[PDB]
Amino acid sequence: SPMYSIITPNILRLESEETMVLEAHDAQGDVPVTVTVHDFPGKKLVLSSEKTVLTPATNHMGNVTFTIPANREFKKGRNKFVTVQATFGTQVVEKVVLVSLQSGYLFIQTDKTIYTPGSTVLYRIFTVNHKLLPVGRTVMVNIENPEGIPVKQDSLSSQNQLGVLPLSWDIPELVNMGQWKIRAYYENSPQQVFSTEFEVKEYVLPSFEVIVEPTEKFYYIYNEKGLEVTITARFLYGKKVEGTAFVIFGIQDGEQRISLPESLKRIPIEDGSGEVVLSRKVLLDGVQNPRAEDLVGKSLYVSATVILHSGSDMVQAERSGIPIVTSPYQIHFTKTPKYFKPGMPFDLMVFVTNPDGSPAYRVPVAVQGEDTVQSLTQGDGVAKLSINTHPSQKPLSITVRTKKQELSEAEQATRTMQALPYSTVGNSNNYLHLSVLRTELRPGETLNVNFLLRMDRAHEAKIRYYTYLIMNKGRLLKAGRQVREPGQDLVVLPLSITTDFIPSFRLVAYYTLIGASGQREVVADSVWVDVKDSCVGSLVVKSGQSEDRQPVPGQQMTLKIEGDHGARVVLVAVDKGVFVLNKKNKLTQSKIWDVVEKADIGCTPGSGKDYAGVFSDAGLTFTSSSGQQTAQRAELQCPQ
Amino acid sequence: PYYNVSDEISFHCYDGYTLRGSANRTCQVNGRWSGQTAICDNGAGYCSNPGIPIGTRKVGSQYRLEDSVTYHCSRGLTLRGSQRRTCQEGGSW
Amino acid sequence: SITTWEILAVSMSDKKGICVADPFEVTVMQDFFIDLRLPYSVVRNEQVEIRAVLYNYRQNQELKVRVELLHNPAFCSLATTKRRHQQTVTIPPKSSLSVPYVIVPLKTGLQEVEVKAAVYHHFISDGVRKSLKVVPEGIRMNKTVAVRTLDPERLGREGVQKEDIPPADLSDQVPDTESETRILLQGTPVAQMTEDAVDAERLKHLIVTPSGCGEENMIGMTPTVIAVHYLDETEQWEKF
Amino acid sequence: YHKQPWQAKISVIRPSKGHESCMGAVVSEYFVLTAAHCFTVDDKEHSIKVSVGGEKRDLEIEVVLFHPNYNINGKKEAGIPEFYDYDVALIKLKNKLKYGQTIRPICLPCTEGTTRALRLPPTTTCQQQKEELLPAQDIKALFVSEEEKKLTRKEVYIKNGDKKGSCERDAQYAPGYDKVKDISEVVTPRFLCTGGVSPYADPNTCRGDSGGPLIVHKRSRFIQVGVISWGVVDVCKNQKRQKQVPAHARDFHINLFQVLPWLKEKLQDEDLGFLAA
Amino acid sequence: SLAVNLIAIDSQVLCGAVKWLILEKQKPDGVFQEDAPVIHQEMIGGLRNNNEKDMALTAFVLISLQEAKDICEEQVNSLPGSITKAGDFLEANYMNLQRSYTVAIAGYALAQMGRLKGPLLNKFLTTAKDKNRWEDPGKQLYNVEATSYALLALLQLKDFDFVPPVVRWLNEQRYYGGGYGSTQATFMVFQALAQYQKDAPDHQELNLDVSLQLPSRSSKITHRIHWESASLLRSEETKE
Ligand SMILES: *[C@@H]1O[C@H](CO)[C@@H](O)[C@H](O)[C@H]1NC(C)=O
């Protein structure tokens, strides 16, 4: 009996094009398909209707893309769904999918991070879709005071403006000092609101900056040497600072600060630098707790203050958040799947980092189980392990440690996780693993995707092809097949990494056959892979002058701009003295992909409890005419 | 540091600001600039931005109602007109 | 300004997309210059002291500078319209010198302070003309006149409501000073009503299998049909 | 008390009743600018009466000149019943008007007379005046309304700044425009949007106020820049004022700077001195 | 006609039954008459006791037709005519009803036509005791069902000022349907509460026309506060 399947993202987005994968297993000849999307509840037709024919020449694969309105009928609380229906001649296959009213992303850029009462706040809004592309939309912009009460509300439209809305707000002389806020959102999505803060305060731009960098990005408890902190201070124009410094330490509990009056020093700043050391004695004297193992978990903060010999300027710096851990490293299996395959190899995505949160470079890791099996941590701070699994259905427990030399075992880090077996339809023990050579992928290179199969030869000859799909930023980038002749336990897929996969992308591969006794079985597998996060195109701004010397106040200089063609570039020059009092809320490409990545329709790093779980955990809805459909998704965001 | 005769200068407002008046002005023989005064207003005040005539110095960013602005010329120059203008009711200084 | 300008660029391609460039710093320095630093605001009629620091970053060359503070009717220094309050000092190589200046803001508003300085036997000079606010002597107060509540039909009449507001006291107001009155309006929900829906956990019995004759069939079909209908609107298939 | 000499009251008698109630504005010694939808091809000259200066009698007209591009029924195909694009028309009287303390013309855009009104140099181009009268901001204008047989001024704001789009898209709530695909098709560039709640609560135009002059009071002078065309929500029903007006009750007008070529041609023999440009 | 949004309903069957009621079982008066009463007199709900059989039955069948009007508008061409006939009938006798039940079921039938105004609308509202229930002395099935029809009528008339008391009475009575002869009560009590979850407002009319005039100013300062533009700080400064 034929089998008409359908695959769509777990959550459909409005004002966008969602891919819809059509398939048939097996049937013959041409089979017309009429896709019709209704709302919900009620069959209020019609949102979007598409048509296509499945020709055996294309191995029976459809490729239709519909655009869901938008629509003003989608207006508080609860959620909204649409009845995605697909007719395959006579057999009708329908499945309701969750809808995200979201229109796209909004990024707000302010010229400065801090303003003085009387000046004007120059800020622009970028209107881009879920693919980070210029789009004309209607946006509501509000400006709330430090008391979170809107004082100004507008409703601009990036239509015919290339997704760039230049704006400004005059700050009255008599204004309430504090942390103001600029909130914005699409008119079609009042629930999805973006925000950017800016401080309003009476201040004056200093003449120099003060940096405080400890010898280590953390602090070892039993370290008798103590906490050595470097005091580097130089003018805003490069030259060094000659003066005196006033440094003081303190312990920071849970949202609490206990200053240490005893740890006060006065180190002279000669040649634009200084040196201060916090004796381990004073540190313990601060708290009224004899045991030093009680300080494990807390943090330290440094408060320095440089003053010139002329007494004309005085800058105050601070370095808070100094982890006092016992191990200079940490371990996280957040990138490691929580499901394994009985008998098949289980890969681990160890994520070793530093006490502060920065990735660790070259860190030997191993599992309590087998020795010798080690892998030096790469640059991004990710290791590659691969332990073996038993055919048993017993939950898998892994304990990865750090065999870092020059460090005792009592000063190492450890973390234990747990994986659950992959349920098989009818206990036929038919699994599928997707091993990928863990390397820092870069747009333009090539990737090798492996397809490891596990099953008896009773039905291994029926497996003649796989079906891989590319998940990217909550959509279907590409979908194809992977030929396979009976006898091949492992095949390779020549995948070409482009500039689209950025930042990350998921890969789901499944195979269908008739095992047991006329029973239709479906087995899938997913894998999350990260790519070098970078600009889609390119944009560099260097000097146009022939090097030479430094410019003179009131001189012309050539400003070379190497950007993309047909692209609009918006500039903004800011004195570094501004970042001295506040360097937060700075628009960075890292933060852009950060928002996009934390919006994927997928949650599980890979694999699931079953076949219908692999799709749902990856961001796809597989539904056939035989009866095998994926789990229902109601909540917009990911569980927990 | 100084503009000779027949010297040209151009004005250009920032993003989100409208430029009214003459964008390009040339120093004439009568020791004055051609065209009108260049003003960059955003149009957010009750009254339009009074602007800052070439050679003067305006003190007051607020253009609300009843608000006022003061002007001051450079050393060696005589201020002609009003040194203080108040935004009167009806959108007019 | 003598400092490092951090230029930031942001491209918006209709093809590629959005991408912010890396900060490009531009250092702007000068061999000899003046760093005039003034407070955010100074009280009128109060004698303060501004510090003008003259920097000399010449590797090995002392400078004979003659700094001067220009006269200004808005301030009261030792410099008049006929006298020039100026000193003659020698700044050592690779160092700086602070030149004290005592003044007295005579009138409020945003005033202007300017200092120039030239070196001897050289073609080098510099000047700084910055501004500082002059806050009127006294204290910043904010007498709350009244806080009325607006809601016709309840405290109104014929649909309209009149509310008079007496002028502020300002009895102890500083002589010769301005003051504004900030009237402020704001709505306030008011967002109420809307009743709760019956929990689906209480409807785990309306799922009856339709059966019987021409009448009994409908009787057994009703509890199921209307049940699903109510659960589709309340979206309570979660707890059910 | 009659501080609106330019103000004109138009009435068109039709079978059964009709009494089409519109208003115009004296622009010359013969012509009186007004709306175009207030009249039809069927309406003759003997059925159209115009009264100015508050005179009890009715002036006999000669011919009503409609705009060459006026077609209210040129959008029924797209499902658009109403289309007030280029909603302007002149009314050449049969007799010459003797100007008094009750009758007086009003400044029209791009004229040697308006140039002096704005106190701008004679070398002022038409483009310069449009930047002066209609800047890219929240313009402060006003129109004449009739309440209890008494003329009264209504200060409003022209949404020509960044609040322009917000005021235009509200044309969807208008009767018949509830099913329009692209809202930018019913609101041509020949429209000036007014009324609303931001920045202030601007008074709305009534049915009898239709064809009324959109004046900008500057330099103690009155300059007409628009003509009352149509409104989103009818707030006048010959009883009382709505009072409970929606936040989308906008009012649209006709920018004279867009219909200049038509005005300059029809008023070539009125000594108004229109600029070339 | 309600399960059309859940499963596949043959138009030939749905509209077929509608055409039969119209052409066959409907007199020139627009009244529907019962010829073969169902064996189960408990599934008919409040039609068991027939003090006003004509008004009740005609209203019941009428409502069913209007719920399938959007569907059988293509096939059945005499539907609009039939709907009007029954309407003219109910409106001519609505001022003579005695039972609170009949008033509710007939009121909702006229509400769908918007023909429930004036005296008729006044009677429908006053009938409800304590302004929250259309109860009749005896049984429970006849009470909950009646109030349900009235609730759907209030929501149809968009009178959400009288709805809260009613909806509150149903929820505070806790009737999860099911049981003997609960065919009508169940299908109606959940149909009304489900329809209520869609038509349920969120607040109250927020439209303040606050206009303040200052002695030192000619024109007034008019501001309107709507639900959308609420919690907005609209300030006005005055140096005087
Ligand atoms: C009045 O102003 C001062 C200065 O910011 C502030 O401390 C105080 O809280 C204000 N009072 C009110 C009523 O907001």
Image (cartoon, coloured by chain):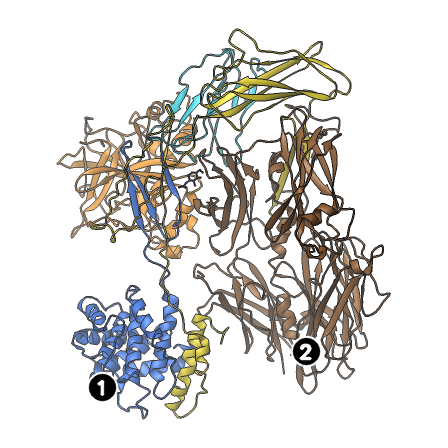
Q: Is residue E1 left or right of residue D155?
A: right
Residue A561 appears in the picture as rendered: no
Q: Is residue A153 left or right of residue E127?
A: right
On whether ligand 1 comes within 8 Å of the CB at mark 2, the answer is no
Please state, as top left, top right, bottom left or bottom right, where the C terminus of chain E lies in the image: top left
Above/below status of E71 relative to A184: below
Output the chain of dot 2.
A
x%, y% of residue A535? 67, 48
Q: Which chain is yellow?
A: C
Q: Which residue is mark 2?
A: A423
Q: Chain D appears what colour? A: orange
**Dot 1, crowdedness within 10 Å: few (<14), some or many (≥20)?**
few
Label 2: which secondary element: loop
| Residue closest to the far right | A372
On whether ligand 1 comes within 8 Å of the CB at mark 1, the answer is no
Residue at the image point whose x is 85% and y is 56% from the top: A405
Residue at the image point whose x is 51% and y is 8% from the top: C81
